[PDB]
Image (cartoon, rainbow, N blue to C red; front, side, top):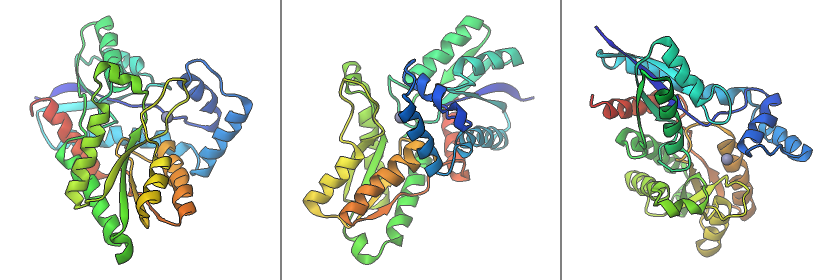
Length: 309
Ligand SMILES: [Zn+2]
């Protein structure tokens, strides 16, 4: 009696093994193969954060935990998860084609990134739709942004509360909360991209929920292009913030990301850690959503909200 639907979970993509690093970054760098040194540096970082295999993994766990959860919290629809990545196979078009081939005709998609941006989300969505329109006999309703879904906000708030709870009294009274997301070229402002505002909004929601009156919005992981990127970068923000007020502890909430990937384990847990360690402040960075039940239910609700269920 159930209606079959495709669950197109989209993401970035992540190397599966060390030997993928090259083509992965080459894809990311639009056909520009990293120099031998970059390559060696990149392998080192991945080794430094615990290896690669666990990364691509999380996304797979996120898709399937959601597929099963959605299939048990309601009995009108039976979902079948499909992973569409951006920089590695299975690519978005690939997933779409598979669904079509499997006979899917009605699908709903979601990107594993809370905030909407013309650069990423709109693109993954427009690509998924043009693939379906190309094959025909397949429609897709795409979720644009879910950074504001209450259960998702609740997740970050609860983690932050525990982190502040864990602090000594003197740190609890002199800490700084740094909410962040992947940086993006400033040019997106040309199109009125809500990305920056959604981040600030995520930051206002979380701080307000955890009862934090001292916090700042920042960006990280910016790429390499002549044109300027969204800032200030978390490294400079921390140092500058310490410079003017002298916070004894910093809390990083990379709300933009949903798991333990490079951008967090290294760019946060190492780069920001280097700076807090230099200024003598304490480093804190709450557990990422990953495939945890609480997170899956939030995503599940977002999908059901998108369907009017
Ligand atoms: Zn990046």
